[PDB]
Length: 225
Image (cartoon, rainbow, N blue to C red; front, side, top):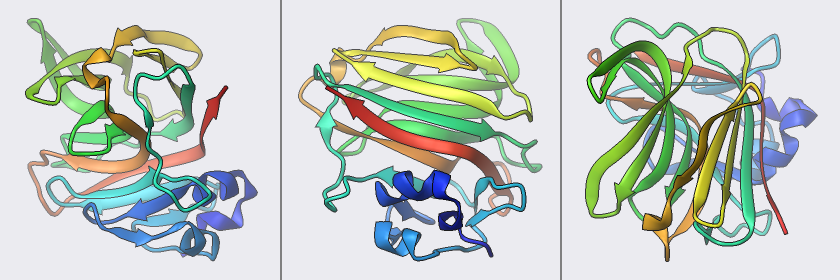
């Protein structure tokens, strides 16, 4: 397998990441990734996509945001400093039995995802069913398992620009340059710290042997002061 590190467009984000697979345990740290880490679940395609692939319920092949110092990313979820994740993602047609795949997250430093962006085979929101869409899920609180869900985009196989902007207790998502979630409130994470994630996180498959698969042509995360 060809390593994503062979493409300079990924050098910086890999320097600022560690790879988790198939669960929360890190399999490759930044220096491992930069030294050519590659596997069936994480490799560079011939047309220069970083592809994540994983099977199993709640299993993942996922990059977790890091500082170049080796510190885990842990920024104030609702602080004044803006944190931005940008990715160009091609979501292929998912294999039979794959029902939801999380491709980007804002996660707190414990057990709660602030935001998941995920492809879903179907979803029903306030009595409206949507099929084959890309979704934003924002948990209502650490002690509230419920979430506010928002359809962002009809699923396409085409390469799509996703931007997550977090600042001052609000979170915004743009898709191909169009705001699809405008300053959603995340004050329920006051006092939490946060980090970005990107990859393939397989949610509630009906075939635990099927492979979820997500491709990224560009990926970066930054802050601005």
